[PDB]
Length: 602
Ligand SMILES: *[C@@H]1O[C@H](CO)[C@@H](O[C@@H]2O[C@H](CO)[C@@H](O[C@@H]3O[C@H](CO[C@H]4O[C@H](CO)[C@@H](O)[C@H](O)[C@@H]4O[C@@H]4O[C@H](CO)[C@@H](O)[C@H](O)[C@H]4NC(C)=O)[C@@H](O)[C@H](O)[C@@H]3O[C@@H]3OC[C@@H](O)[C@H](O)[C@H]3O)[C@H](O)[C@H]2NC(C)=O)[C@H](O[C@@H]2O[C@@H](C)[C@@H](O)[C@@H](O)[C@@H]2O)[C@H]1NC(C)=O
Ligand SMILES: *[C@@H]1O[C@H](CO)[C@@H](O[C@@H]2O[C@H](CO)[C@@H](O[C@@H]3O[C@H](CO)[C@@H](O)[C@H](O)[C@@H]3O[C@@H]3OC[C@@H](O)[C@H](O)[C@H]3O)[C@H](O)[C@H]2NC(C)=O)[C@H](O[C@@H]2O[C@@H](C)[C@@H](O)[C@@H](O)[C@@H]2O)[C@H]1NC(C)=O
Ligand SMILES: *[C@@H]1O[C@H](CO)[C@@H](O[C@@H]2O[C@H](CO)[C@@H](O[C@@H]3O[C@H](CO)[C@@H](O)[C@H](O)[C@@H]3O)[C@H](O)[C@H]2NC(C)=O)[C@H](O)[C@H]1NC(C)=O
Ligand SMILES: OC[C@@H]1[C@@H](O)[C@H](O)[C@@H](O)c2nc(CNc3ccccc3)cn21
Image (cartoon, rainbow, N blue to C red):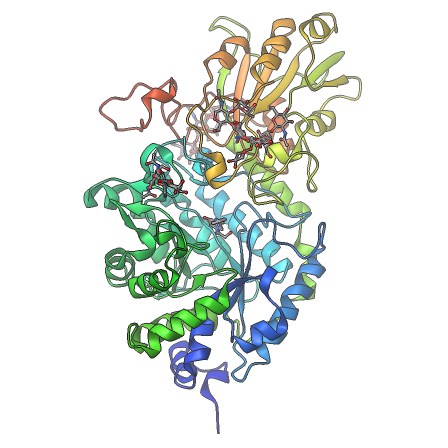
């Protein structure tokens, strides 16, 4: 017989309907199952008809693996999936959230908070375009990005993953989506999924909804706000995402007024699917369904029932697939979950797969391997890092000479601080490892390396990680650049009620700035207690988490370009003010949202 779903010339909806009508319950539930590469084998993928795989943070084939190694791994998994009766290709997902960040040698872009500081949606679109290429360089077809959380309290460990506390800025930055996926056609229906083809990736608007609204910024906690507030702060960017054809949406671990997002039928089905007319697939977060219950995982049968009935389509299991499949099959066999619900979930998963061309190009393109870490992409990351920088102070007092820009020619200069020569620190979380890491973890340029690359050949550059006051005072330095701040963190590990930088940080700044005029570069995922740093410093720059391209920092420090970044968040006076956002009745910032000093290029 002619087999319609295998015919590339046929309309997506026709191909979807034709395939679905041929599938067994096992094949259907298989599609709904996403597993870690760590538990995947060819036999597992074939025998369970698995629909998707992912790499969680740090889930890599080998340390330092090449783009070709990634492609071969993904293709090996694909070969097993394509060998099933129906030959439905799997989709492979990864957190490419500031470049293809799990991958050695991948360009690492500034994290979202810094991108918000640029107020440049086209820049962010271009980052999406570069990121898609580097993801496809590794054979991967699906990025879990953008995070369109609106972080309302910087005590949250994921505040750096939010473009802004201002939903309007977050909405503007949804341009990442057509960068990753390609621009939607003129004739496009909001809520339909879209991916242009094999050189683009499926995107994921996350985490639905109100992940940035939790009490005290406690990660995965309760967002207590009325529907009006939910709809005017936390929801708007999802509509923009719909308009731009985002292929998938990931559900939040958080709760809204005490109801777990992973169990919320009203919002997932009633709003996202039925009101926004989202036609892509809805994916859980990692063990998200497990965490519906307290303790987590204490009634997995309930978890499966609650999440599938709420309207989730694909479950990021990610390990215990046999149990997931067994429980879901049982619920269907028992009449507890209707076939219509399974058919809806599979319709959505297949729609995204057919739409993106997965059935036509299930395997990697070896010619794309060379896209990884391309200099053109690094030049883009360098531009972004520079544009993200916010100048908070430039001259110890209002009558002082402006410190920045600094001269490239001077007899001797000092570069200092825990963050001056630490690539892992300047990248932050979601870089090589889930939580990020310390030291030379990938290919890049540290602040020290950037300084050495920028200055006149006659200028002697001295590095001291934590020099004492006497070393600085007696050193014969013209000026110092001192870089300090937060260590890398991700999710709950980043939750922080005090928001003061680790030591030595302030002590180093005080020692250096006490001995010579100094420019302090603050590396952080968020505003942190800054008055003491300000007091010691002649100039201070909030550099956020600028990524692999340290020359973005020096491009502004030495005046090749002027400072243009503006705060995308309120800078508080103290943590006891929190939460405190622009528009609040009590608004007493140290620096308001939108604050930023400027310089002109030399
Ligand atoms: C304000 O709140 C902050 C968050 O709540 C808090 O930071 C946390 O402090 C706790 C200690 O109570 C840390 O937990 C421990 O971490 C130890 C190792 O920590 C190092 O390595 C990790 C990465 O693995 C980094 O994230 C850390 O920053 C730290 O880095 C090291 O820091 C040194 C000092 O600056 C550097 O010289 C060094 O180079 C650097 N090394 C690296 C690799 O970067 C573990 O050994 C412990 O076992 C413990 O881990 C916890 O164990 C309990 C378990 O439940 C947790 O899951 C597990 O995390 C925690 O890492 C840290 N969180 C951060 C930084 O994100 C502030 O504490 C201050 O700063 C820290 C760095 C310490 O110096 C504290 O003494 C100090 O008080 C809070 N500040 C205030 C004012 O109270
Ligand atoms: C010395 O520095 C100052 C301060 O940075 C320069 O003036 C700024 O120039 C920017 C670029 O032209 C102006 O930004 C633009 O603003 C308009 C109107 O709002 C807007 O339509 C543009 O899109 C752009 O806004 C940016 O868009 C991209 C975003 O990423 C970014 O956040 C937005 O700012 C900016 O308003 C202006 N600031 C002020 C206070 O005047 C100045 O540049 C010189 O003057 C400006 C007015 C312009 O004629 C430039 O061509 C000119 O060089 C600079 N001086 C020199 C000589 O370099
Ligand atoms: C928002 O965060 C708070 C604070 O973490 C959460 O409350 C906490 O809930 C946990 C269980 O999820 C409690 O810990 C447990 O305690 C029992 C002993 O009674 C122990 O057997 C378990 O091993 C576990 O340690 C904890 O007591 C509780 N903390 C507080 C301060 O109430 C809350 O559930 C979160 N809300 C949401 C919606 O996620
Ligand atoms: O890495 C996959 C997802 C990621 O896309 C989400 O943005 C993020 O919320 C996320 N967190 C985890 C891991 N969470 C976890 C849960 C229970 C135990 C250990 C880790 C996985 N993921």
